[PDB]
Image (cartoon, rainbow over all chains, first blue to last red; front, side, top):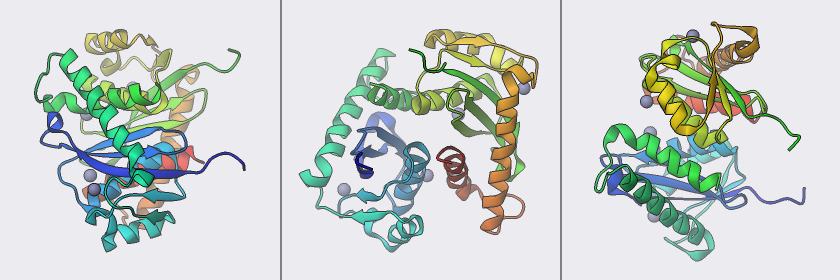
Length: 146
Length: 146
Ligand SMILES: [Zn+2]
Ligand SMILES: [Zn+2]
Ligand SMILES: [Zn+2]
Ligand SMILES: [Zn+2]
């Protein structure tokens, strides 16, 4: 019982080295500090739901998800998806230290790690589409399995 | 130290409810019995590598991977990818109880679970492309977080 609470913080951040699909949906499990990230072409309610569907398969179901006031997170579409899963949801103005400083620090570590790995294979600007998925999985791996 | 060994068994299995991308690459971690699955349009060396790239981000790096004698698993492409990662590889004739009974039992539980969930949303034959990914992530979730 007395071991910690399953609460996530999720946000989208922009990363042009991953273009065309340059919207990265990033989720930090505030307990374990495990990071889940996925690639998306557009930030929509459906992009938020598909991401969380992946994160649940990976981390398991959380009790609550903390996001900001973004529409993709407050639409009726998403409110219904979360309800369908029984996951509480609490908003917070963009970046609100309370619920966003972690996922924001995450954004940075992630983009840094994407740059290091990309430049190491000699990709200085955009990563070729066919290597994006493998490069993102490696970054995610490096950041979680420390 | 005296806690168990990180050895995987991987195989592809065919699932037409997931068409066009109906080749499911399935990996069982023989220690934890955790299951990783991904969708692929064609069974190729590159389909095996992309899958394992996902599984590593999810489960961490294994010491060895057991497959059968399939070409996608013995090509020079894959031998080099595995070497690049430092993961030993041991083959076994298709299905060889030794290294395949687990991933074969996995194949069945997975396809059963895909059928149950699909028919529950009223998809009796093929699952609509736009719901495949979410349905597969749920099946994977059900089978791992028991
Ligand atoms: Zn999507
Ligand atoms: Zn926002
Ligand atoms: Zn692929
Ligand atoms: Zn085979």
